[PDB]
Length: 110
Ligand code: HEM
View 1 (cartoon, helix red, strand yellow):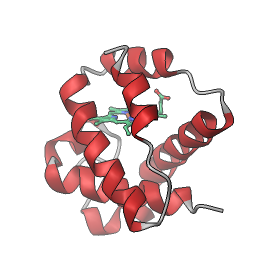
View 2 (view 1 turned 45 degrees about the horizontal axis):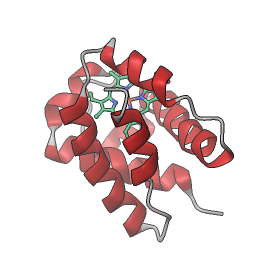
View 3 (view 1 turned 90 degrees about the vertical axis):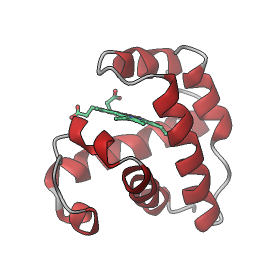
View 4 (view 1 turned 180 degrees about the vertical axis):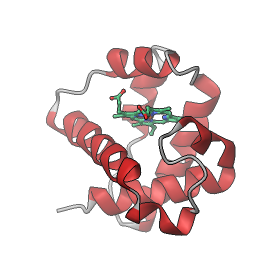
């Protein structure tokens, strides 16, 4: 398998390194990056992102719904363009397929 859990962990390391302020929107606001994996709010959230990736791969991803929910948190195109870059790094680091098309689908609804 691809270890998508590991890809997602590196995604968040990249994301919050480049944009620490994005972490303020989550239940793990203020938690040291190096300790995120031990945080309960983070574990649940990371699991859902993994689920979304597996839903995209499996053909059931709802990009319109995901976009709508993110707009509902005042998260928009600029943030998802930054996420796209961080996710490409995380995928590359693990020899995982690029997920750019999945992010482009979300971006099309933003
Ligand atoms: C690769 C890009 C991203 C993916 C695949 C993704 C996916 C998800 C998923 C699956 C959830 C779980 C709830 C739901 O399904 O709506 C979620 C929640 C959330 N996302 Fe993202 N997201 C991405 C980028 C971002 C970015 C850049 C931000 C910027 C702050 C963000 C902010 C949030 C917030 C605030 C929540 C809710 C957290 C909570 O309920 O406590 N997302 N996201």
